[PDB]
Length: 158
Length: 158
Ligand SMILES: [Fe+3]
Ligand SMILES: [Fe+3]
Ligand SMILES: [Fe+3]
Ligand SMILES: [Fe+3]
Ligand SMILES: [O]
Ligand SMILES: [O]
Image 1 (cartoon, rainbow over the protein chains, first blue to last red):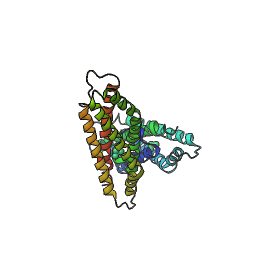
Image 2 (image 1 turned 45 degrees about the horizontal axis):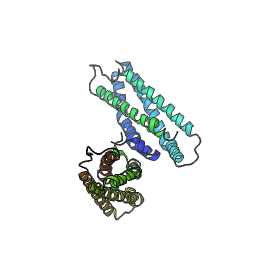
Image 3 (image 1 turned 90 degrees about the vertical axis):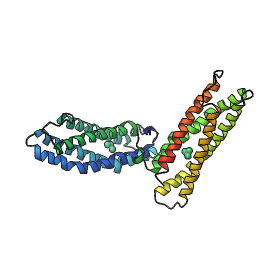
Image 4 (image 1 turned 120 degrees about the vertical axis):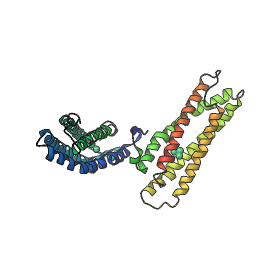
């Protein structure tokens, strides 16, 4: 099995973008209608599901803006720094990306708290259980993703 | 641990170069003196150690020339073929690389036969036991190396 420590900065970035950023965008497109439906249908009975929709939307919009910043501005800066060019704001860039990750992590903590980890009541059927499983999988994937960035990619440039 | 289907050709090549090629060159530099000393001290009364020295040398020079060919000429062609440019000898390239790996593999089975699968005789000590340990691990390392190229890297482009 392949050890990410041997990748250099630009391969680690290509890997992140293929394994994490693009599947994340696609899962967001696919999953948001279901979160919205769950809120619309059972939110009146259960107000924590409306809070879940809004926390999920905030989580999603933050992640999309964060991945666009990484793809368009900041990952290219890490690559330039690895090649020997002068990059000021390199620790500014790293610190803002770490701040973004910490915020995303606390939103995941909140979503999981809202759903009692991701345990659906016996009242739940179909769309409800789908949303819970997908949100749990999105949390696992996001944890792996930001751990790769924080403890491998950023350590190679700091 | 990485999933190779998200590494493109360029990144997987960089991976192989950091994880196998450069460590293998370092290990050849460090291990050769010990092989030469084992054959010089114990070779006279144990001629299979002299045969082992000559087989190891052949295996090692073939590996070094083969990795040079991949790094300087053939891996860049795999990357160009991934990137759409015309590389009308790609299959020739892959066939010669596969044939090289076969030849190396057979040199390894020979080295293993000479050493009874790298288990030292009782009367061996020190340098003799060191050489068998290091050769055993270098065979393990080389099989992984060759399997990654043959069955992951070369299948991305053929
Ligand atoms: Fe990211
Ligand atoms: Fe990130
Ligand atoms: Fe190789
Ligand atoms: Fe090779
Ligand atoms: O991220
Ligand atoms: O190789």
